[PDB]
Image (spheres, rainbow, N blue to C red):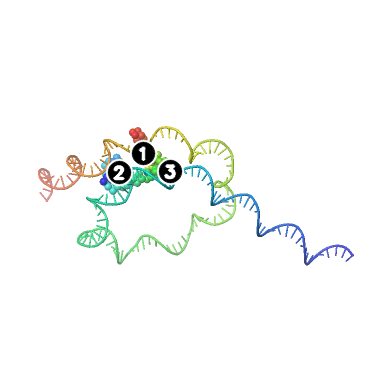
Amino acid sequence: TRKESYAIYVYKVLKQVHPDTGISCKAMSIMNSFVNDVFERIAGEASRLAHYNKRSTITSREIQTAVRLLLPGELAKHAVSEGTKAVTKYTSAK
DNA sequence: GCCGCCCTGGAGAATCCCGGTGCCGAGGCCGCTCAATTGGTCGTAGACAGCTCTAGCAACCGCTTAAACGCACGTACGCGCTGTCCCCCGCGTTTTAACCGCCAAGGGGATTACTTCCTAGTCTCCAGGCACGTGTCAGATATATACATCC
């Protein structure tokens, strides 16, 4: 049975930040739970933001506002940067 | 004989009650009006059945061993009492700014209606990324055997 997860992406991000460090299966379960929880929080806040403004679509502005609302302080400030240029790079390609 | 002082009766004005009439809050009625209802059609979500494989469960075993438990002692700490002093509370007096009512113009933003176009949903086809399994390979580890040496 094909069970989807964020395992390989968390592993390759780990190899970016720590190329000689491994990880255990329980820590990967915790990382998968963290990514799913943060995805659910940001998507729910963006859904509420689209509902309050009478908009039928979720754009990058809603995700940016949800990140500013949920992420505390400087963690938002870099992440709002880290999303934006990625969107810009996507605009440079697609 | 004339003048001043005390006692008692009926008429004029203030107040309570009732009836006619006008004004505030709320409900019935009417008109618009848009969203719920009804009727029909169709696609698919989910119920049902079937087979396979793995986890759980009730009740028992046996062994090990570390945790739990009971007890004695001792001493450290919770708690009560007392003093003290200091800081917060109550009150009187003076200030002061909140609050309410006012300009004066201008912009922000909520609606209503309208136009337009870009972008995201949908569909079809395809291919490569992800998941799983395996052959192979270099680093780590353990020992076999030969050489220098102390007693």
Indicate whether A33 appears above or below B3.
above
Residue B133 horizontal/vertical position (percent): 21, 44
Residue A20 horizontal/vertical position (percent): 26, 42
- Tell which tag, 3 or 1, sits nearer the viewer: 3
Does residue A79 appear in the picture of this structure? yes
**Where is the C terminus of chain A found, in terms of image quarters?**
top left
Q: CA distance from mark 2 to mark 1?
A: 19 Å
Q: CA distance from mark 3 to mark 2?
A: 31 Å
Does residue A64 appear in the picture of this structure? no
- The amino acid type, in three-letter code, at marker 3 is Tyr
* Residue at 29%, 44% in the rendered image: A4
Q: Toward which corner of the image does residue B79 lie, by quadrant?
A: bottom left
Classify residue A3 as left or right of residue B83. Answer: left
Marks 3 & 2 on one chain: yes
- Tell which tag, 2 or 1, sits nearer the viewer: 2
Q: Secondary structure at mark 3?
A: helix
The residue that label 3 is drawn on is A52
The residue that label 2 is drawn on is A6
- The amino acid type, in three-letter code, at marker 2 is Tyr
Mark 2 crowdedness (10 Å alpha carbons): few <14, some 14-19, many ≥20:
some
Give me the chain letter of mark 1: A
